[PDB]
Image (tube, rainbow, N blue to C red):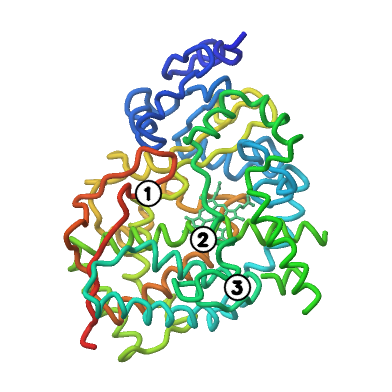
Amino acid sequence: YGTHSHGLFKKLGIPGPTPLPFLGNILSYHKGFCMFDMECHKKYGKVWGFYDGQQPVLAITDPDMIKTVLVKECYSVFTNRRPFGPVGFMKSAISIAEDEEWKRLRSLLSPTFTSGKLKEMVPIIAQYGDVLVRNLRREAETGKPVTLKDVFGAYSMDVITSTSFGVNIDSLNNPQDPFVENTKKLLRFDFLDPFFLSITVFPFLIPILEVLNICVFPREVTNFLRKSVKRMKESRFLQLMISDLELVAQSIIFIFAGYETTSSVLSFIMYELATHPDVQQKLQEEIDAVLPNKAPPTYDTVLQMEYLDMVVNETLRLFPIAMRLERVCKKDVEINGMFIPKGVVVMIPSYALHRDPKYWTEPEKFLPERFSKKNKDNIDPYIYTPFGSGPRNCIGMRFALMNMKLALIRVLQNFSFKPCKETQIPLKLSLGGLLQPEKPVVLKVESRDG
Ligand code: HEM
């Protein structure tokens, strides 16, 4: 044994890197997830396979197959994502839930993320849009070059607290440690770090760890928050959901999926507006045309912003946070002539696709015009997929976008961001399992006549 699934991609006739005995193909992750995926797409073509230990992963690319798994799948065959380390009571989280139990939660929370309940949340988010400008004004006046993800991570926190349970606080290094230390600890998992890398190789550990009540969502923070929710559940997203303890699972997840996820994207965007100060100028004017001098953004003032939408999307093109998109093959099935067997993890190289000469010309270039209607809609969904596609895509995509734009509005309409000393140029991506800069983005911020 040690090499269970290795007979697969040979007997099936699918190309790919040849695996070692217990590791299979992991050492290839020495460059990262996206790095490994670019190489594989180039070399093995449109479809190939590799082994995450003894777990076979088939990477598809033909948009025809992509729609069939991301759409023709509601229990059909594909439906769940790869199961990871000891989850504990979080096995009730919607992003972690499976099969019928998932469809329940999904179609139960959907109401909570409708337009109308969003245009209703705007007021609140705007509130923290202004706090951001205040806190950003300090670092401008002091003349010290700013570290992005810190102000954005604070903004993300501010909006997560208030919208998840109306807990209004000024996270941003001000009353920085009330109920903020817990929340602040809910970061994305780096699946390429020692711990997870081991479990991927030795999945038999999961049942072992779970008996020792070791969970991948630290008991410390989950406990705090589970008791908090109960507190205000009595005092009374929380208000809309309001099982009694499945509710605590969702609430924590939204924070997990929206926190470091938003500030991470936002910091990337402010980076592109540095050696694209020209783009920032256009954006700035577009914001002033719609909203007079420092006019307050409205739910609809945002939708009417072609350029803002172009800058955001093109940023998400180059940097699709969830590098990959994968689903698990529930049963044996063929689909568009291919045949994938039960238990195989179907992967979709989001980052690699978003940077492949086939659909993008000079793909390394940050040029917004791609999304202006004329270049726009000449691009295939299933190819550009930052929030995924189909039934099981980002349930909070719009919210994510609103939030990120509102943050751009007030910010752009008050400051100008230009590079400085430690500001890396070009970029350089980390070789870990998270799509981050590697050496955080630093930008000098100056007030716009203030
Ligand atoms: C920069 C912002 C964000 C990006 C790029 C993003 C991206 C994604 C992606 C790519 C997926 C997987 C889609 C798929 O596999 O088809 C996903 C799932 C999910 N996201 Fe987000 N997301 C963002 C923000 C948020 C926010 C703010 C929330 C909070 C409501 C959220 C909640 C979720 C949930 C619950 C799922 C799981 C859905 C399910 O399996 O039913 N996301 N997101």
List the single residue furthest toward the top. Answer: 1
Amino acid type at mark 3: Thr
* Crowd class of label 3 (few under 14; some 14 to 19; many from 20; radius 10 Å): some
* Crowd class of label 2 (few under 14; some 14 to 19; many from 20; radius 10 Å): many
The residue pinned by badge 3 equals 163
Q: Does the beta carbon of the residue at mark 1 sit less than 8 Å from ligand 1? A: no
Q: Secondary structure at mark 2?
A: helix
Q: Position of residue 436 (x, y in %)?
A: 37, 49
In the image: residue 290, left or right of residue 187: left
Say if 88 sits above or below 118 in the image: above
Amino acid type at mark 2: Tyr
User: Which badge, 2 or 1, comes first in the chain's sequence?
Assistant: 2
Mark 3 → mark 1, Cα distance in angstroms? 26 Å
Q: Quadrant of residue 233?
A: bottom right
Q: Is residue 339 visible?
A: no
Q: Does the beta carbon of the residue at mark 2 sit less than 8 Å from ligand 1? A: no
Residue visible at 70% across and 62% down in the picture: 109
Q: Where, quadrant-wise, is the N terminus in this rendering?
A: top right
Residue 436, which numbered label? 1
Q: Position of residue 231 (x, y in %)?
A: 76, 71
Residue visible at 35% across and 61% down in the picture: 267
Q: Is residue 191 visible?
A: yes
Say if 179 sits above or below 441 in the image: below
In the image: residue 242, left or right of residue 26: right
Please state the quadrant of the image where ligand 1 appears.
bottom right
Q: Where, quadrant-wise, is the C terminus in this rendering?
A: bottom left
Say if 301 sits above or below 393 in the image: below
